[PDB]
Image (tube, one colour):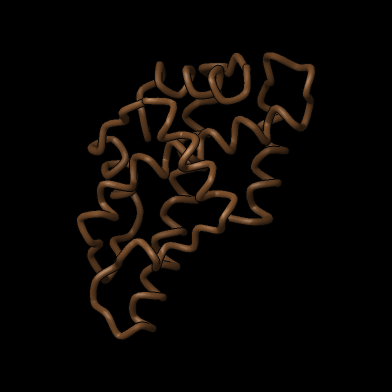
Amino acid sequence: MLMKVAEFERLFRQAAGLDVDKNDLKRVSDFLRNKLYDLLAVAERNAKYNGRDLIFEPDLPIAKGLQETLQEFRRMDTALELKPVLDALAALPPLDLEVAEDVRNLLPELAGALVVAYARVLKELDPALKNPQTEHHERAERVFNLLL
């Protein structure tokens, strides 16, 4: 998974006051891993367009809102390990281009930002519910699919 079960739990609680079900975490991890991979796939296309053979941060399609969510995640002081994120991404097809060092270091933070945004979307679907179940996750995925 992108991070430890305890880290996912902590982020859902910190970001949105939600008690996430441990049973839904593997699906959350896989879903967000796919979104992160797709940010890198688009970044690869952008790097090539700019005549480069390496992916830099500006190549990742990060809109202002997600950039602000990333800053908020950074300020939660949650140091996520790189290896689990790289291992999760390696589960999918390799990209043609490698990424710059600053991008590699940004990956765990982007994984955390995606969890913060996902938790907050899940909360907005039912502001009063503290313990969302699988059905709510299906709706949160549909929302994420519209933009990422």
